[PDB]
Length: 101
Length: 106
Image (tube, rainbow over all chains, first blue to last red; front, side, top):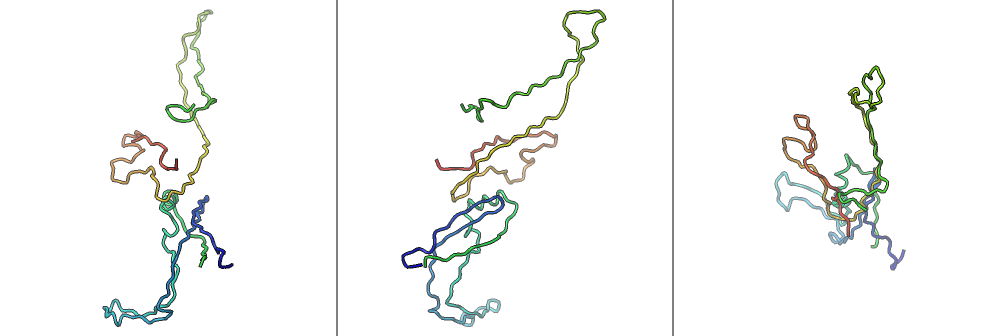
């Protein structure tokens, strides 16, 4: 939408409805260049590990986004509010946005 | 006009409900006597009373980050459970519980 126009806003909040809670979290990320844009084959041959620690795989130049911890979404106050009042909980839906590159 | 013991001061509070047993006279004399009755049939009454109060709540809207202080039961092996009966059937309240646990900015 242009150089001088922001493509999103800071949405960090928590709304408690009767039987739902919606948690929003905005963070600032930095992404470097990994591997000099190369795909590299990695293994344990140079490591000289034990038979239990042997591996073979690949390192990509990509990074990934991870929000698979509860404190990425709940403040400690929100967590206390949830656990002191609810017999159970589960996730229903999510929205992901990437903005202001 | 807030009561000094605590609570809600009401100009028209919940009214007093007053109850009594209607007197039942005992056997009157055969001849008339204008002296007021003093001999009554001894009686009492029993029953059930229900009170239902609707209360309006004012929910917290706090943006505080760290967890709040809450009223909690103590987790520990104890001879009794708080706010329960004992082996004799006597209900007891171990401590007085106030209301001010959540916080808000001044």
